[PDB]
Image: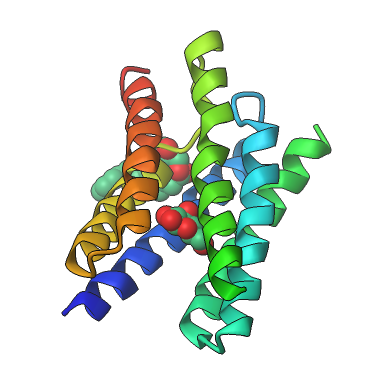
Length: 81
Length: 81
Ligand SMILES: OC[C@H]1O[C@@H](O)[C@H](O)[C@@H](O)[C@@H]1O
């Protein structure tokens, strides 16, 4: 059972960044978003992805690749104003 | 080694929400933050914490409790405008 819980948790947590991507790409506004939040989160997802490759856990690699994508675009928009 | 990388990743990801908490509690502005993002993220962290209890993983429980706190504060401010 627990594995299902984990998969649903990872899915939810990864796709949650998608509406934030949508809003950032639609309104082109990033004032209220923390830069440090997405910097630290960037490095965090990077290390989770390194942990996934180190453990050859493809589901962790996938979820964190999608998250790294989302977080990267959001951070880009933040940095570029 | 891998365990260290995972722990640092969890740390980074949990503490990343702290600067967003700070900014939201100081400027009292949440316009550019996605509500749906933090809803899905909330439920995701809840399921991560349920997975930690189910696997008796105290570090997962602790990290996800701290994250649940931060995400709850941010979500509250967003829902209250
Ligand atoms: O990818 C690493 C994941 O760590 C989880 O604890 C968080 O819920 C997600 O924000 C993040 O995507």
